[PDB]
Image (cartoon, rainbow over all chains, first blue to last red):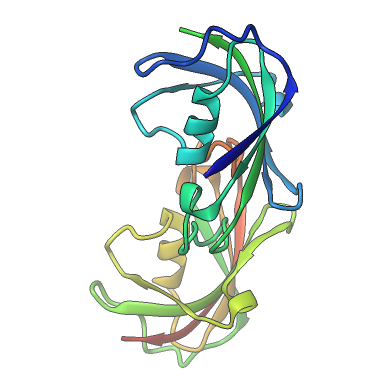
Length: 107
Length: 107
């Protein structure tokens, strides 16, 4: 699963519903906090629609639990990330990921 | 595309053919040499079917020019990897990758 740990509160009432487009600022890391990719380095918010499996399960499900303006740390288990085979070349097998995500807005 | 630079020679005759299974030991890293994943960390060779697009275009197209027993440094441009979009959370946009690949055998 995905363990969500709030860093900054959102509005607590505007949560992502299926079909909407999530505008976020993320930072994907390895279990120990090793930075891999951050949309903050490009100053461009990343968009993804709920129900389209555009991102990994824990990435999306962790966000569905957040309200607009919130920023939290999402600890994703391998089964919710890239599983037992991982993504050969970039992601090793059985990898737990830690994302720092901020739900900028919905659309 | 991909640039093949031989670190160690192969037999120079046994080249991969569509359908065969390529057995390799790799180490994928970014353009500056930062390591991401290595099958050697698990002492388990990696396998992929030639022509089945089971890996990024540069990964596969480099091994197709390698003979059994050869170990080479493959410099893969962004277009032959994850492109302008990359792979959000793992690899950033316009990323040149560098793989150290060893063609252990064909099967």
